[PDB]
Amino acid sequence: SAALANMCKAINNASRAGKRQLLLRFSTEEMRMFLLQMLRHGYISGFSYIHDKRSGKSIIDLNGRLNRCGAISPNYIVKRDGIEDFRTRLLPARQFGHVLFNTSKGILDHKECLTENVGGKILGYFY
Amino acid sequence: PGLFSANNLIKSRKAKRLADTAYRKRALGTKYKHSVLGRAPQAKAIVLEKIGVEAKQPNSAIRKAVRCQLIATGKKITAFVPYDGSVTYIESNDEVTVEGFGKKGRSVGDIPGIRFKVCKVQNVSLHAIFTGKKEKP
Amino acid sequence: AKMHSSGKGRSGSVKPYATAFPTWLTKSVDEIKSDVIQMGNKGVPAPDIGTRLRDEYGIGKASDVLGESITRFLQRNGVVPKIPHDLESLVHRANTLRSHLNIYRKDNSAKYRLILVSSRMYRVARYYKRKMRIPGNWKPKLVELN
RNA sequence: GUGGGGGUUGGCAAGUAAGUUGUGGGCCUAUCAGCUGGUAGUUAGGGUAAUGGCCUAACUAGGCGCAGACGGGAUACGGGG
RNA sequence: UCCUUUGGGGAGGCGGUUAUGAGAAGUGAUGUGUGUGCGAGUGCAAAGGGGUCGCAUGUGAUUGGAGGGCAAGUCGGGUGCCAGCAGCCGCGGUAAUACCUGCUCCAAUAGUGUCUAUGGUGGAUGCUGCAGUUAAAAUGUCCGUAGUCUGUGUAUGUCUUUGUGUGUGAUGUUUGUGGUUGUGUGUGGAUGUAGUGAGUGUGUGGCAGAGGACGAGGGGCACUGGAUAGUUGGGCGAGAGGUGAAAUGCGAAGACCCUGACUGGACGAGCGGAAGCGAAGGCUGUGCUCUUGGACUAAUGUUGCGAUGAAGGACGAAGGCUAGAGGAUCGAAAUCGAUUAGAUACCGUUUUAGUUCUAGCAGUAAACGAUGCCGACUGGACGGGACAGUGUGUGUUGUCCAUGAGAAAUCUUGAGUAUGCGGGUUCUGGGGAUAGUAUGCUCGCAAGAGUGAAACUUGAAGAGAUUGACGGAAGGACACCACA
RNA sequence: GGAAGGUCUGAGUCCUGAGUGUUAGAUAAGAUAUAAGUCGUAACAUGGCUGCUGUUGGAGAACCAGCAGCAGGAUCAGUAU
């Protein structure tokens, strides 16, 4: 989760400069679960990663649609009744944005966690 | 600030709080040690002398005060007699009730060194004698 | 990001992805094994064995000929040193500083080196005791300062 | 019980009450850092309505501590509120 | 109402007294008194009260303010830096919108002001969520244990156990604070399900070893260069030295200057730089020797052995102190001569401790880039130093321009990466002054260092920049009230 | 305990030793607010000897001198035959 926060600062830097692609010289397993949840929601075009028997590599394809992404350290523990307070602190409006949690069913955003009756540890957000 | 670090944060933030002066008098239990009337809001006293004090410049004046004796603790204090021509109702060996000024234990205005204020004179309000509602003692 | 200095250099080797077995070998595979096991008996340290294999035999990765690493091969053949090479180089460096300081007392430069060299040796010893490679009561054998 | 020796009618089960005991919690303070002799334990007996150093005899050398012991201070009855 | 239910009960009930809080009505009105008094009935153990009727009857506002903050007067008359007012800023010296007195108006109203404690105000204690180049604040430098972080304690269904409070429905005590009455919620535990499967293999950070180079990094030994001073041979014949100008002081027992020989301590010029090395303090003659560092280059070994760091430890300019050695130059203290109104000073003469080396103590600096450590990411231009390659790369480093940031000056491997606020882990600050002062304790031969208050006082103290005024400030022009 | 007495619990009296507060004292060193002053002029301009930090000696008083350091300076800089 030190690799998750490093990735979000490098994405904010390129999305502000108008880049199309981003190459990072590292790649972890839960860094790739966070990126697969931005792809199915429409915020990036795609990505791909290389195997080199070093720390890994990853290439992100940006879109033009991202306003910001972040990570929360440390990963607090939130019951299913406390999901909704973390949403009013992190997203600008009530109609868009996604807060992601690491639950006992995988990685879900805050709309799914309410339709499955679970809580977990917070990872990050993006809008 | 890890998730298992709450004993390091209570230890650290309690020590920073002592740098606040108002909090430090309460936490160490020494808020009423050096105080001429302790925990009372008003106090009685008997009048020894009747003096006049200069205003602090740039103001020209002479403010009328009295030297008293606190009946409860035997400490000497000076107090200020507010209104116009009102220092002449009191005599010596009179009893008087004094109270604060209202600014946390500092002096107010151009009056140097005085932290108290005469309120009554032998159980009669001093402000009512000046407006004509009551009669002098 | 070095341990005891602010150095940030990046030099060093990079081994290939997915090597193979050498065809250009001149000797036999069984004639090479009996020589890696000979040099281990003369007390040659394992980082220096791999430098002879590379420079004189054509073996770039000995895990493709011996079937495993160098110091696991020597172990099955009954050659297990009393202390590993990492730890014993550091005892030896800390003895040559201690006996220079016995003749030249005013060398304040070497007295500072002795502190850093020797706290690096107690950190490496603590690792081999957690891992059960030396006894729990091992002490370094040291020249005695005067 | 192949002798004898005690007691003077006092019970059972529910209900109600009471005693004893384990762990856990933000008053302030390091110009308070080392503390402890029935003190930590074992074995026997006494006492108790009842477990237990609760108490005694003999023997072992233990027990607590920067995750704050042992001390000292301020207008300290604890909760529901 | 209960205990002991016609016995007992200062438990408990009933009034009275009191600006304790909270709620609800009044102080009038034109068609036809919201008050007070009395009379019936009701009520109670006996009575007050209250509400259902009638009879007369007619009464009932204050407290704090009017210069700004802050709603409301340059209205009359008095006083003249007086008397007084004013939480804060401020007013008053014969021209008071601020004091005293009279009118008029403003806010709330059976209430409205004052003194004291406390929540908010305060992102001015900061978990969310502050600041630390110059405003208060990163510690002189490395090493390092506990702890934190990294490497290899969760959610939820069902059941159970506990609140007098409270969230939220219903219900015309005439309305209301209320009362009655439906439903939800607070802490621990038991038993299932899900995450959840486990060490393996690989070698990404570090460490250890290899190769050829680079460096005023350190200790020791042996030599060397000239200048200052002095001793001693030869020459000369009256002043030399230093100052704004001179005086004390030195010179015919021959100074100063020029020459042949020697002795001694200290120092290492020029080359010498926005060049190198060391943890920092610091380090420039030559040759030997024992030790040392970082970078680079690579199909070597190992396999996470790591980051930060109260407690502990070592090192640390100059001055000072303790013992021995040494003594060229300079020089506190002392002393005379000048200058001056006076100079115990600046300038000078005579003369010391000290300045050097060896062995130690001590522990401070504008010990400064006034700028924690580690990790991720980011435009150009011209350079330097080392290594390796061949048209480039890695580690370091100087100058100049954007973007971005900032209170600005300014910053460019950071003082950048959004109040769009969370990468790991420490320290220090919380208006000024009292004061780094008292007192206790630890260390020192001492000189002192480290840690570190309060009473009392006070409305600003401070940062960066703007326009003026001034300088016993620097330039460029000028002029017979300036020179030639 | 037949008694003389023994045992347990133990207030109180008399004496010594720490602690934690509060307070009187001849003399006497500071701090702060004043008045109304006396003596000088250390700092701010190259403030008339540039200024400041540490250390050690000295003076009626500000302060002065020696050794090293800093610019928050009065210099971001000047022609190698």
Image (cartoon, coloured by chain):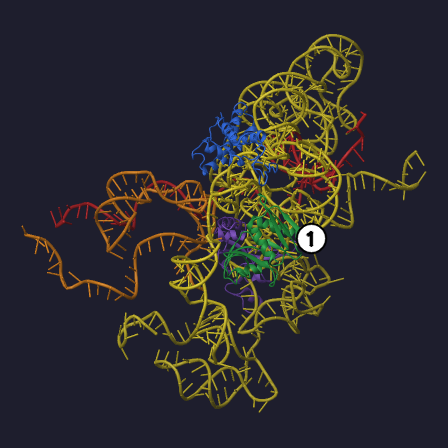
Chain colours: A green, B purple, C blue, D orange, E yellow, F red
Report the number of discs.
Answer: 1
> As displayed, is residue B19 above or below residue F75?
below
Point out residue E162 in the picture as x, y percentages from the top left corner: 39, 63
Please name whichever residue, B111 or E171, is drawn nearer the observer in this view of the structure: E171
Can I make out residue B108 in this image? no
Please name whichever residue, E27 or C79, is drawn nearer the observer in this view of the structure: C79
Horizontal side of residue B16 vs E73, given as left or right? left
> As displayed, is residue E449 above or below residue D75?
above
Q: Residues within 10 Å of mark 1 (few under 14, many from 20)?
A: few
Please name whichever residue, E9 or C145, is drawn nearer the observer in this view of the structure: C145
Residue E248 is drawn in which quadrant? top right
Residue linked to disc 1: A18
Horizontal side of residue E192 vs D61, given as left or right? right
Q: Give me the residue at 67% from left, 56% from top.
A: A64
> As displayed, is residue B69 above or below residue E261?
below
Q: Chain of mark 1?
A: A
Q: Give me the residue at 61% from left, 55% from top.
A: A69
Element on which disc 1 rests: loop
Can I make out residue B126 in this image? yes
Point out residue E461 in the picture as x, y percentages from the top left corner: 65, 48
Point out residue E180 in the picture as x, y percentages from the top left corner: 42, 75
> As displayed, is residue D23 above or below residue D15?
above
Amino acid of disc 1: Gly
- Quadrant showing the C terminus of chain A: bottom right
Point out residue B24 in the picture as x, y percentages from the top left corner: 51, 51
Please name whichever residue, A61 or C98, is drawn nearer the observer in this view of the structure: A61
Residue E88 is drawn in which quadrant? bottom right
